[PDB]
Image (cartoon, rainbow, N blue to C red; front, side, top):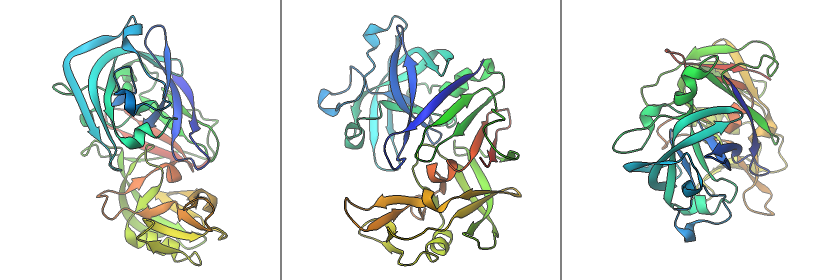
Length: 330
């Protein structure tokens, strides 16, 4: 089997992308944030504290003939940005772009933090990291991909995120029309539960590529590109007027600047992020100061190849027995 679904930016900055997901019988369609940096599929629901729901579409398990309560099970997750959610657990039929998994754990939120409430466009998350990170207790549950894997024509999914435009998540096949040139594959470590890999270096604008190992994670659920302070400083030093602002929380630059591209290495191959992808717009409405899309990972504890990087590539998440990542230009 295969599936193919369009993913759409939630706003004009590509802060996140939402993909429609059918849950239950008859289907209830919710727009979920596909997150290769976590491993829980959780949704706003009829059980979510009413005051914490503001515009989201909710899952109502009592209206699904296929919903089953997982007795006594709970879940609770905290993300890197300090947001969180928790609740109880159902299994139900979940379909993505025509691909159906029966008995998928659907984690129903009883509580969500303010960041989730305040974002009316995101009805929940669909985790695509390794199932070892799943937070269900007492027994951990499998991700949608892990459950679908054996049925897929090939044990893969691909992310093809758009710049200020829709893109595609495919399951079970590689669309050879969706990229230019060849896909370069690189090793993955699952030791921390992530799609963790080692980039071979970077270049700033037209500068010569610097060969250096950069360990990090391919994370569709993180907006920006977070890299070591040395790398990030080298980038912003090429932008007139750019500076790190402790009050704003990162590198800012004059909105009138023309940003250089940023290149990262995948083996002997190279992915070029255009300068425009690195512009995240005015720091506040009407400001002439803009927020940068490449920021330091110091204090996160891990480097993160988030949407700014991933949207410059066609990315293969190969879930074979020995997982790998593939990157192609597009």
